[PDB]
Amino acid sequence: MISKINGKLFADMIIQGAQNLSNNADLVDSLNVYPVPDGDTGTNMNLTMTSGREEVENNLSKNIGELGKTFSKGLLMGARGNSGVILSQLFRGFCKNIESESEINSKLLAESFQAGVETAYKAVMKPVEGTILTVAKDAAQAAIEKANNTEDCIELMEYIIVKANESLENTPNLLAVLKEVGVVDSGGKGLLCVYEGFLKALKGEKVEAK
Ligand SMILES: Nc1ncnc2c1ncn2[C@@H]1O[C@H](COP(=O)(O)OP(=O)(O)NP(=O)(O)O)[C@@H](O)[C@H]1O
Ligand SMILES: [Mg+2]
Ligand SMILES: [Mg+2]
Image (cartoon, rainbow, N blue to C red; front, side, top):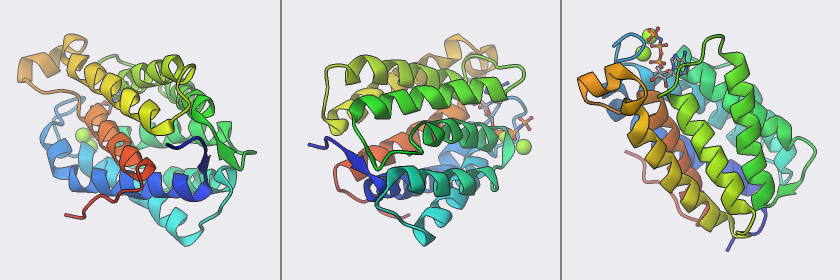
C-alpha cells in the first residue's frame, strides 16, 4: 500500500499519466465533436501534458510541493486548446494546494483534486456540463468521500477511476451532441487516461510506450 506520495512518486504519476495519454491520443482525437468537431482533443491534451512531463523529468525532487511547481509551470506554458488549458488549470490548482508539502497522504490527494476542480471552473467563463469539468468534479467528490476512510492511495485512486469512468459514461446525458453523435466527451476521456497512468505509477508499474 501507499500511505504517502513523495515528489518522485508524484513525478512517476505524471510520467506514466503522460505516457498513457500519449498512447490514447488518437483515440481521444477520434471522439472530439464538441465545441467544434475538429478531431484534436487528444493531440492538444498530449502536447500540454508532455510539456509538464518534460519539465518534471529534467527537474526531479524528493519534495512533492517543489515537483508540483515544476509540473504546473510546464503545463501552463505549453497549454494547447480548450482541453489543454483546462487540464493545465486543474493541475495548477492541484499543485498549488500542496506547494509547501514534502509528501501527501490520501486525504490531501483528494483535497488537491478538489482544489483543481475549483481552479478550472473559475478559469472557464462559461462552463458547460458533460465535459472534462464534470468528470473532474465527480472524480474529486468521490476522492473526498473515499479518502475519509481509505489510507491506501492505490485503493483511493482505483475508486476515483471507477467514479470518473461512471461520470464519463454519463456525459452524453448532459451534452446533447455527445448523445446524438454517439460518443463520450473527449476531454473527459483524456483526463481518464491521465488518471489511469497515475494508478499504474502508484502500483510501481510502467505504461508500455506505443
Ligand atoms: N465551456 C466548456 N466547459 C467545459 N469543458 C469544455 C468547454 N469547452 C470545451 N470543453 C472541453 O474541451 C474539450 C474539447 O477540447 P479541444 O478539442 O482541445 O477544444 P478546441 O479544439 O481547442 N476548441 P474548439 O475548436 O472551439 O472546439 C471538450 O470535449 C470538453 O471536455
Ligand atoms: Mg481546435
Ligand atoms: Mg477540438
